[PDB]
Image (cartoon, rainbow, N blue to C red):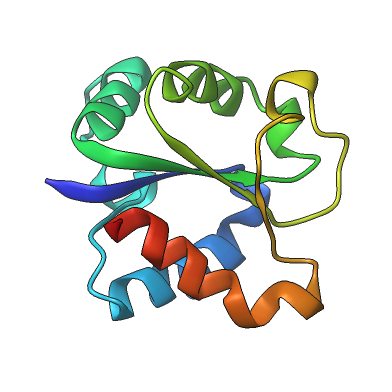
Length: 125
């Protein structure tokens, strides 16, 4: 099983894999990332639901491209019935329904010293 699933737009994949997943895995956190862990020949919705239901938390990597991505949006809605960890990766118009959810602001350098601490602390409780 996975500790966390990552929901993200492909345009942000560089940072997601090389930074976010990298740091999580270094921290011993077991991470689901579609391009590795998805099952080929399964339907998209099947792999999504597998990931969420076999994960304790869902990370959502917010950006302008995220909010234009259909697959990303569908995943979020289901994630709201569990626990999500929103990360503000790039500034964007956050939709109303994440607009009242506390997030991690990666763009906020002044809050960078506690970014990873808070993320990891939340996943492990």
